[PDB]
Image (cartoon, rainbow, N blue to C red; front, side):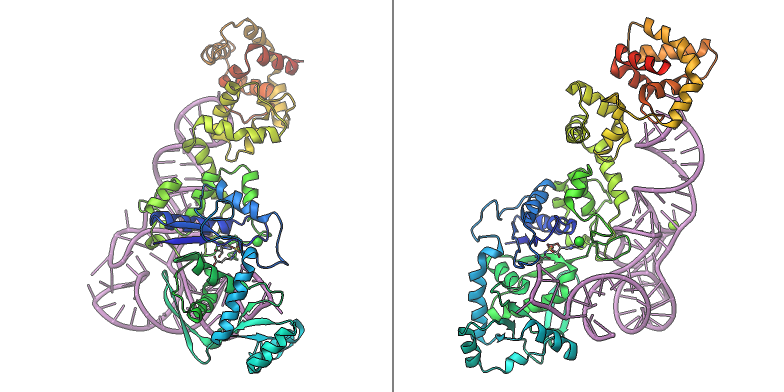
Length: 468
RNA sequence: GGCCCCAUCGUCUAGCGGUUAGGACGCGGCCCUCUCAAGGCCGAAACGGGGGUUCGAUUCCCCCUGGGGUCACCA
Ligand SMILES: Nc1ncnc2c1ncn2[C@@H]1O[C@H](COS(=O)(=O)NC(=O)[C@@H](N)CCC(=O)O)[C@@H](O)[C@H]1O
Ligand SMILES: [Cl-]
Ligand SMILES: [Mg+2]
């Protein structure tokens, strides 16, 4: 059938590139009624960042993905952490040794640096060590690595499902280290052994790996295994076209979550990076994505990750895809994180409704609608100016307001409209300064809905401090 | 620098021999209107260069340019 996987490396924050690739693997597996695996590639102890693994697993679930086999969901071919499979790689590295497909190299890091300076890259000198002496020197505990014994001279063909066949000259393929002197494997060894053992048949990873692929094709041969299909995706980029990175862009998924980006939108956005719906539609669900997926509709150029369009899409979701109630729920954490409180669910909901079209991130709601939840709100210089200029007519309106019994948006509007008429003045000349008195701002939702919201007492109690 | 991949508006893209080269973000204008948004309408904005193939190239082939990847006991 079809078995795909995402093989994150726990070395930092949950990378957006990781989500991007995981999405295409998830779609392809489901579209074929296959399996989607998660394998944690923690083989480099120097770059290992404790706490990374949980964070990446949480981020994929947050985005809406699900996996069938993995670290925390079990599976027939585990463990799903390479660090727990160490003995396994040893066994296969030694098997290559016997098949004559690899050799032991004893050079120190320093000698290798020197060889690289003279000949540029390892020259395979350890191949000239009699196999018996190599084995003997190993039993003595002498530190060493196992390298892939590339067939020289020759040519190695890689088949990319998206670009056709690409020919590599074995002279372009180094005798890569398979097993490190600390007994840990290199990405190359672990990847093939594990992809094979876990049944993967469709390898989808970014294009940065295409040139390493020939090494993998040769490993599958050395073991006498069948190679899976390869699909190399384009690399997400910084605005300056360089491979996306933390110094020039936001690459951390936990950053997007903390900024109030809806996971559904971030997901939707990531799908338009190298893929597009038949009918050009750009707002769609994860389920529609799976259903429409097709390699024929994948673009191969490296897409710039545009934060502005992401904000736009996030706002589109907030106002057209989610219900008023879903938005009101997702806003709470951000209200709490801002130290604001809401009286009740009804109040919150109405507040969110009034602001729905005025914020693109959940974090912006507490910011722009602060005056609706606390009395501790800023007053813009522009709002203060408009307040003083209209102070006189607000004083003449105050008594009319205190007299008003039906505190409804409809009633209030008819009241103020009439007040502006009799005073021979545009509603705006009385509506603008009242807005500043109530909100401390000049950019808010409709006055009547804002006036009604708090209730007669609350609204007037604030209008009074303004006239004071 | 060697090797490999890629190439339509500023950005994400549709196109898959013949189109007024379409859509989206963003940008400008207009309508809406009590502010700001949201929404609607209009607009400016692209096929990197040179060869070919073909009646006919954005599209098919070659070269150059640009961008990216890799040449690590990193992934
Ligand atoms: N800027 C970018 N744009 C788009 N995709 C990007 C990316 N950066 C990383 N990726 C892709 O995300 C997945 C995991 O990245 S990663 O944590 O560094 N780990 C690894 O690359 C290796 N553990 C796995 C390689 C493989 O899948 O065979 C891998 O599929 C990797 O290719
Ligand atoms: Cl990074
Ligand atoms: Mg145009």
